[PDB]
Length: 222
Ligand SMILES: [Ca+2]
Image (cartoon, rainbow, N blue to C red; front, side, top):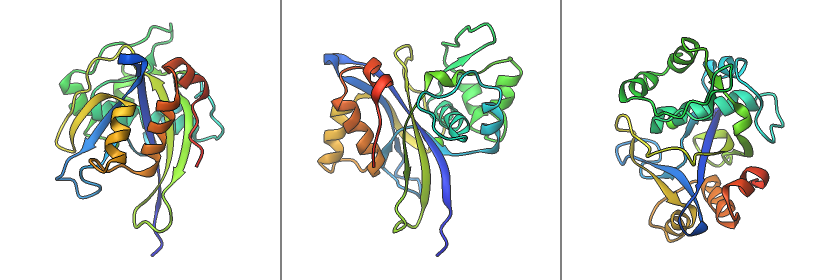
């Protein structure tokens, strides 16, 4: 009756792909999940307390940040992405050297234990996120007609350097780089379910000529 509106964030990782179309990392929730089984989405999830702590050690600020919680939510998005697909995006040290390697299976497994695992892994290394590599592209609150509600902050970043996503555990049954047009058609046709914000991001990416133009202009309006 008095539904929690859960703060969350999602990361839309893109690259310039085949046929001059943008490609994006998507994941699919396993049929065994209790909430939204089989839904396609981008990596993301609920805010954790260590997210704002890591944001205070971060470099820079998200492009098109408008609110005081944008740095913490950018971190939420980056953390959830590392847990889901095994890559830590936008990491650097004090000298500006970028991390460009994936997490080993064991480090991804350790990050999925939750708590302050990511904050600890970064702080043992003197590393932090460069939030300047993310663009705030939207904010969506689930309609009050829904029994489970989120207030989700969407960020965009470019992953032209990334290899393949790697899963940990059973929550997701698939993860891949897909042209945004391909995925959109599959949702519009009814083949795969997706929440409204997911569709609206895919349509924005399809209208966009390339990843540089997206990092300069992308915005999802309700
Ligand atoms: Ca997640």
